[PDB]
Image (tube, rainbow over all chains, first blue to last red; front, side, top):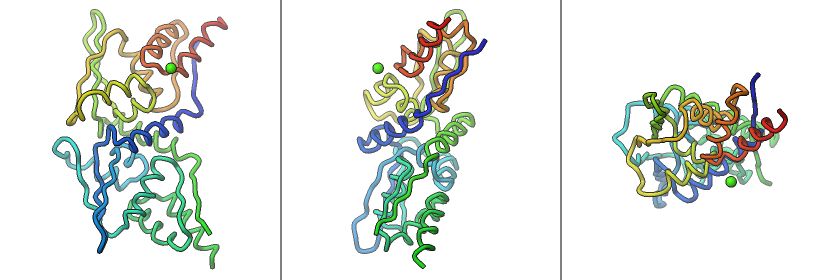
Length: 130
Length: 129
Ligand SMILES: [Ca+2]
């Protein structure tokens, strides 16, 4: 005989704790430094695994080579802090919420990190405004 | 107007990748060394955030002390490797599967790491037997 059990809510509970840890700045091993014209650089701390889990681009970036130990700082250009903030929040929560006139720029930021699900959703939202 | 989107399956997909990373032994920042009487220590590579997300014991263990630089090796005693394996698998997949006659020792491990859900399921199983 075999005992089996699965907790249906597990991955949502778990992500809830991981997001708490991100906001507390605990266990974080990467800092995203986001530089946008004529405004100060912003910093977002996160966990590489979590970014990897949602984005093949971050996955490739953090499994390639092997970086000298500790806090990695990654320079990001071409994307507003607030777009990156929203992609990060998506990785950690499963949700994103954006002013309708800026959906195009979020989409492009999701393109850049190959977050296909938010690329599609953005796209479908733009197509129903035609 | 506002644009709103949630991907309902996101957290299952993302745990699927995190689990692949664990099995490919990439990005790992902790190696558990599990020692058990008259058997050599077994190693298990995992991601601290992930273990912390599923176990307050792991959470406390990795948030206490200093922001560790790189791979930490951690001695563990009082749990067979295979019990730890199944708890780690549970953390990363939401599922655990064990032969009936060892449910008790799995329950004990889940108590040790304060995985409450698997404690309750193991209890439930042992009472209706
Ligand atoms: Ca408890």
